[PDB]
Length: 148
Length: 321
Ligand SMILES: *[C@@H]1O[C@H](CO)[C@@H](O[C@@H]2O[C@H](CO)[C@@H](O)[C@H](O)[C@H]2NC(C)=O)[C@H](O)[C@H]1NC(C)=O
Ligand SMILES: *[C@@H]1O[C@H](CO)[C@@H](O)[C@H](O)[C@H]1NC(C)=O
Ligand SMILES: *[C@@H]1O[C@H](CO)[C@@H](O)[C@H](O)[C@H]1NC(C)=O
Image 1 (cartoon, helix red, strand yellow):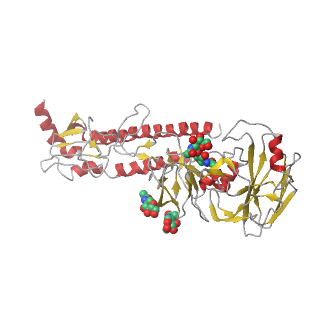
Image 2 (cartoon, helix red, strand yellow):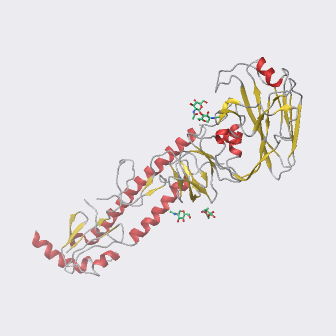
Image 3 (cartoon, chains in turn red, yellow):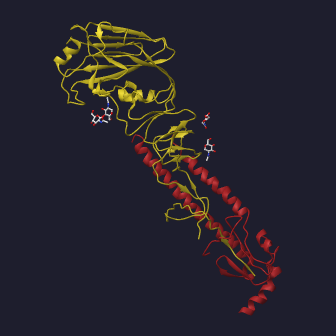
């Protein structure tokens, strides 16, 4: 997806939908939850690990390397993060993309254009991980084929 | 009838670093350093440091006359001397075990200056009034350290000299004396009359004998002679003795004291305040639960580990556009 959302509120990532009802933003729960559960967990374990020895150049030589050793620990977990969430954005996208399949158009940009009419509890249904391809199959196939 | 997917672009501007891209801006981060300080030197937990403006520790403790006014106390959290504090040993010479002394005195709970050998009472057979130099001017006239007396032949005889002090105070007693090495044999003879002159000093913790070295050193503050400055801590119970046939610069004032686990000596032109803190730095103080800092190698009390890195910025969250 080619951009972020200034209007996002409750969290790091989620969906923005305009249906025959209305429009606007929202975000997920567990995906944002277990995100930080893993992140702050990582943020700790890194710095915690540095310490010193007792594994059973005054400080001038030691220090310069301690730093050099430490500085990179960040340049990692940093790098390992911007990839982490990115992975979680992909994962968000695809979990819907497999769910809907033929039912909605992938215009990309995280965006789907529903062939059928989706309104809430169908929406949240998708979100809950429970969405009926059969329920909406025809409602889709008809509208989709007029296009082609 | 769409449903889309996107993410947060934060009002927050702080940028961090990655392998493939350095400058990169993010929504969220954390900084493990502390750049920032109150730009002041404070009372450390309610106790003020000691500040010697134009004096360094030596001139102060010796009682250099340029240190006459200065300040006092029974107590100080730490010690601060400025970049500008030049008033040292005005008679040229080496201060001995200086660094060690500096450390003993960083933090003090009780500090009591007493005159361990009264100038009037103590030295009946030697001359206690000649002891001035132009090397140590005060008020436009020849002078000397306040805490020592430069003793000189009364007569044309400089008899043998022994004085003893028992420490009846409650604490450690810091005692300082010095040894005069004059420039020429003639010089030696005028002062002490005795070419053979030696000096001895002793205690439970201390024993040393001294021979002066006559020789012509380069002129400093007009002195071609030298003066070495020595010291010791006499234990509460302990006794200390002094012998000389010459060349000894006798104690007058000494200090009863009880230490604290050492703070440091901060060297800064930073001003003191009535403020307070846990963690003091040459540049300022720091209130942080923070792990580190790039601020100064030298910290006092409970302080964040020093680090030479520019910036440490992790990532709580994603990039933004
Ligand atoms: C106290 O410190 C001041 C400056 O640190 C000394 O004054 C300087 O003395 C030297 C040589 O005596 C000269 O190079 C400077 O021109 C002097 N400047 C001033 C401000 O007088 C002063 O002599 C010191 N006093 C003692 C006894 O140490
Ligand atoms: C700073 O000052 C108070 C009251 O003057 C003092 O008692 C306290 O120990 C200090 N604060 C600290 C150590 O946080
Ligand atoms: C800074 O330290 C003082 C000590 O009394 C405290 O009152 C204040 O809340 C502290 N601020 C921070 C950022 O912790």
